[PDB]
Amino acid sequence: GHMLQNNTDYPFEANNPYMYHENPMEEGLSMLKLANLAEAALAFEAVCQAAPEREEAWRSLGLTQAENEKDGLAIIALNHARMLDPKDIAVHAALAVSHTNEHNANAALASLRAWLLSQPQYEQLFFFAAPNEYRECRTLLHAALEMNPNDAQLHASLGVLYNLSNNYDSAAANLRRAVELRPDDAQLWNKLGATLANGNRPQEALDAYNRALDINPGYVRVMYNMAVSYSNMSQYDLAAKQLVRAIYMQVGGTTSREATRSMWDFFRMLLNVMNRPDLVELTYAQNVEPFAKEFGLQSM
Amino acid sequence: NELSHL
């Protein structure tokens, strides 16, 4: 028997043309290979609306959403996948990352813990918000690294752990190691960039983001993160240009905002600081075109 | 400064 309603906690997009298609899962996967995340997410939403028992659909949706700068929706989707397959280690890794971003410390540590101990190769094994949980995660990961040295994902996972406690120096070293081992992994470069940025190294962060974008040119979270690093260095032309790219790509260019509404408000702050009150007035309407044109990304 | 995301 089919089940249609283990999905009522997810705010599905209303007018989803993928609901009319024959194989939206296949199409979502194709859109991912194209790096069209907003579009990928809509196709996976269709699958989760029709077949909410398909774990792979929730996993793909979750992964796509966090890449499209929507951690809250990522966590909702991923929790479904986690219920339908508690050994899907990609779901646990992703939950750790999105919870770290959301500053859910207990959930992040629990996700790193499940990530490790769900793998048969490792199952034998003052941070104020969750002190002994953090120490146990550190210990597990270090024990794992002595059984499997030079593992990129253990080093990445230590990176996430150390981001949680603001030990950006140790996080950077570990993620640096992980990208040396896997230099075509866009997420790893992004993770290293965010770590450097959060540790007051934006110039180095931007080098990592460029590598991430050269790998995955539709990686909207990297685009956002570049806006952030540029803004942190007061380079507002560069910030503005990347932020406009991010907004456009996040919504899927030609196509329920919220994630978008704070990016627009952030963009307003940039336009204000650069002394452009005409441009500021335009942000209220939340149309990309004026800014795409003003900032050299499109036409005229 | 503003926060970056993993």
Image (tube, coloured by chain):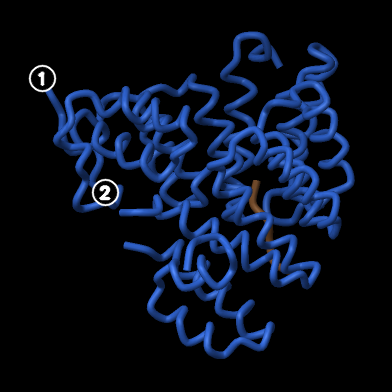
Chain colours: A blue, B brown
Q: Is residue A187 above or below residue A53?
A: below
Residue A168: where, in percent of width, then height?
83, 49
The nearer-to-camera label among 2 and 1 is: 2
Residue drawn at the location 64% of the way across and 23% of the way down: A116
Q: How many numbered markers are drawn?
A: 2
Identified at 26% across, 51% down, the residue is A13
- The residue depicted at 58 percent of the width and 28 percent of the height is A114
Name of the residue lying farthest toward the front: A300
Q: How far apart are marks 2 and 1 (CA)?
A: 23 Å
Q: In this view, does A156 lie to the left or right of A107?
A: right
- Name the residue carrying label 2: A12
Tag 2: residue type? Phe
In the picture of the structure, the residue carrying the numbered disc 1 is A1
Crowding near the residue tagged with mark 2, few <14, some 14–19, many ≥20 C-alpha atoms within 10 Å = some
| Residue A295 pos. (x, y %) | 59, 68
Any mark on residue A96, and which? none
Q: Quadrant of residue A277?
A: bottom right
Question: Outermost residue toward the left?
Answer: A1
Chain for disc number 1: A
- Mark 2 lies on a secondary structure that is loop
Please identify the quarter of the rendering in which residue A187 is found: top right
Where does residue A55 sit, x and y in percent of width and height?
35, 25
